[PDB]
Image (tube, rainbow, N blue to C red):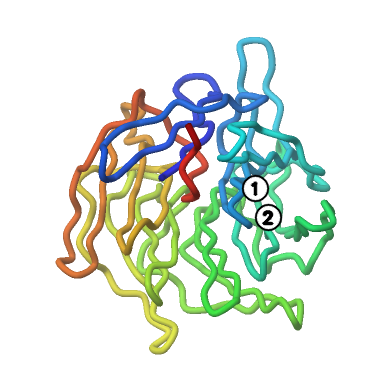
Amino acid sequence: LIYTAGGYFRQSLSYLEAYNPSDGTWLRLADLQVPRSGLAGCVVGGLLYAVGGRNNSPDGNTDSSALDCYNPMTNQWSPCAPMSVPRNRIGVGVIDGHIYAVGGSHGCIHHNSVERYEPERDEWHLVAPMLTRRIGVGVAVLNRLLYAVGGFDGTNRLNSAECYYPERNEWRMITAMNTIRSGAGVCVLHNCIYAAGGYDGQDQLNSVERYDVATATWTFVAPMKHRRSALGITVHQGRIYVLGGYDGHTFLDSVECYDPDTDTWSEVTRMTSGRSGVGVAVTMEPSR
């Protein structure tokens, strides 16, 4: 199933919903303990992790350092050890069963710091910071190297990308994207890194480009039907899925699916309600 967690439709949300690309159904699962937008989702050992974000509520506005773990076999959330700092509009990637939390913001503070979570010790540890402060950063993992793509440094939006080598604990700049993107959806399909949508400081984007490591090159592919920033993204059964986002006017509920063999995007479903800044990941379907 495609799990979407949190989000923001004029207030941060607690929804955890799971989409069945065969059924077309949306399953309503256990609410997040805290409403959160600008968070990220990932999966380790079948468990779904919600990382970072921000609680925008009628009575408060707090960025979040929290890490929480959802088990599809209990339909229960359970808290994990928190990150060293709150990270709204965070990026996350998974390498060797460890969760890397990248960038994000805490109030006026725009992080270049990165930290690593070990599920089997429930421990976070700081690693080398990025070359760039990046909020709304897209993160992907390819050949066990960690890519941070685009974002917003507090003053300028970025098309630059950099790559973290875990065993040498350093970041190196790579080829920059064709397009400046903050709040893009970034994932790793087959053996390429896709960056879709986002915001360049003037327009929400529908363009999609993919990075090939063998050629160290970014190449445009078919654009999405709808421009969107702060979209959710994941990969299911060889196809890219993008969920919601913001198009300058509306919080979208459209879900589009990219088939790399036809280079075609397709609107496949709508979420139960429009929202941006979700955390998306794919894991075992909930029992009973």
Q: How many labels does the image show?
A: 2
- Taking the spot 34% from the left edge, 33% from the top edge, the residue there is 248
For the residues bearing labels 2 and 1, Cβ distance under 8 angstroms: yes
- Taking the spot 38% from the left edge, 65% from the top edge, the residue there is 194
Question: The residue under label 1 is which amino acid type?
Answer: Gly
Residue 223 spot, x, y in % from top left: 22, 56
Q: Which of 32 and 139 is in front in this view?
A: 32
- Taking the spot 26% from the left edge, 45% from the top edge, the residue there is 22
Question: The residue under label 2 is which amino acid type?
Answer: Ala
Residue 211 spot, x, y in % from top left: 39, 74
* SS of the residue under disc 1: loop
Q: Mark 2 points at which residue?
A: 101
Residue 259 spot, x, y in % from top left: 22, 61
Locate the N terminus by quadrant: top left
Judge whether 142 appears above or below 17 on screen.
below
Q: Mark 1 points at which residue?
A: 104
Residue 234 spot, x, y in % from top left: 42, 53
Specify the farthest residue to the front.
288
